[PDB]
Amino acid sequence: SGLYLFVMNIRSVFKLDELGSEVLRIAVPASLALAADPLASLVDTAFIGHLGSVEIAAVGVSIAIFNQVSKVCIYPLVSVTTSFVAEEDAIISKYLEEKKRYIPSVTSALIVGSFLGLVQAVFLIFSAKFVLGIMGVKHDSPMLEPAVRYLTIRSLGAPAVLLSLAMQGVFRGFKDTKTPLYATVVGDATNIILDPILMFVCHMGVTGAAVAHVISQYLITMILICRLVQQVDVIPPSLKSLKFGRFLGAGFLLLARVVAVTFCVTLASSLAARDGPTIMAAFQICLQLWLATSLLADGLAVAGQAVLASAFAKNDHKKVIAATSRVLQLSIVLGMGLTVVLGLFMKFGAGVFTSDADVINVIHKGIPFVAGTQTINALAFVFDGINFGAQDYVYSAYSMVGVASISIPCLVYLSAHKGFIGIWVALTIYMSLRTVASTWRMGAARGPWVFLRKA
């Protein structure tokens, strides 16, 4: 059994050797870029918070529209490209040939991102009134006008947004998270700078905030594409040299997988909402705490994926094994550390979020789940990176379908029976199912780990 990989070289968890330096070198910048958007967006939130009462709820619903539409079109387009570029960049016979280099995954991802980005752009421009009526914004309500304005304008950035996300998948294929991190920082500072200039000095309000974000997003796309064309070639030499069927298929497998994962969390929230606003608010806080702390290991999972995708591309079973073990031990360490920190923060900083004693008390009731399964969470996310470095997409798809089929009845039953604590028990069952699904793929020496029966 492949479970021994969890403890192999455990005297070298923190060693800054080639593997340790590389994993740290790939993982830390990605985490930083994932952490830079929330802070820059919170600065944006502040600027809009000084506009008016309708504008936040107007812009906020407009933003809620974008963020989910993207997450559908983000996770596949980036997790497929990080592996399909890291594969083709690791066997492209690269040598002292001067004529840069064409990678079909790089060209394929840019096309898919550009198409989806303009498609989302047009769609959210024309169905703005429609989606907003869907989004609980009444048509007679005052929110609808600035929401439509901000939505329609910010949808100009949708092409650049999805294109730069494809390019982050590309640059992750090259094991370069610094380039997306630099681009993200640059755009976010520019947007934090452009927000007061346009919203307030130009008297544009929600139009100003949207123009600030769109200009900054197109700057980030520009930065990424200049660095990307200087490193490799993005034009295909012939129109037949584009690997597309394989590309879109992994994307749709990962898209179906994400739909299931997000729907499990969607049901939990829609079930907590049926338990009074106190349970409503407390579960929402717990859930953001739960998931946000999992988002740290996301750079670690990218490093593991890129390294394993490059290594599986070169028949290098020895580094595959070392890197798998390394990121796995790092993930469990981070999970336990986040367990400690998040539990402590929840008990003594609930009052940072809410001024309600009831909400804080329910938050304190739920601390064990949100804090306990943090090691399960880190393992679940890092194994996704690992099994994506193994490029096991059909298993991911059908395994999450099964985890949801087991977890969704758990949610419904446990929630209606024991409310807040029952939803959290169900979510623990689901996360334990997730972790066990991914770990079985590796440890059982089945699929992309069949070679383990020979080591």
Image: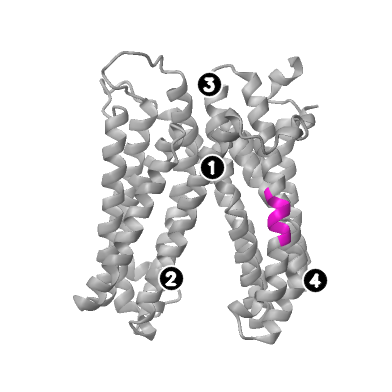
Q: Is residue 155 visible?
A: no
Q: CA distance from mark 2 to mark 1?
A: 38 Å
Q: CA distance from mark 3 to mark 4?
A: 49 Å
Tell me, yes or no, whether the two marked residues, 3 and 4, touch with CB atoms within 8 Å: no
Residue 313: numbered disc = 3
* Quarter containing the C terminus: top right
Badges 3 and 1: C-beta atoms under 8 Å apart?
no
Image point (58%, 16%), residue name? 315
Q: Which residue is mark 4?
A: 417
Q: Which residue extends farthest front?
A: 16
Instruction: Return the disc, 2 or 4, that comes first in the chain's sequence.
Output: 2
Gap in angstroms between the C-alphas marked 3 and 2? 46 Å
Of the image marks 3 and 2, the number of the one nearer the N terminus: 2
Residue depth check, mark 3 versus mark 2: number of the one nearer the observer: 3
**If you read the primary sequence from the N terminus, does the residue marked by circle 3 or circle 4 appear first?**
3
Q: Are marks 4 and 1 in contact (CB under 8 Å)?
A: no
Query: Is 43 on the left-hand or right-hand side of 258?
Result: left
Q: Nearer the viewer, residue 4 or 106?
A: 4
Image quadrant holding the N terminus, namely top right
Amino acid identity at mark 1: Ala
Q: CA distance from mark 4 to mark 1?
A: 41 Å
Which residue does the numbered mark 2 point to in the structure image? 134
What amino acid is labelled 2 in the image? Answer: Ile
Q: Return the x and y of residue 137 as percentages of the image width and height.
A: 41, 77
**Are dots 3 and 2 in contact, CB under 8 Å?**
no
Determine the CA span between mark 2 and mark 4.
30 Å
Residue pictured at 25% horizontal, 65% vertical: 211
Residue receiving disc 1:
27
Circle 3 or circle 4, nearest the eye: 3
Per the rendered image, the range of residues in magenta is 334-340
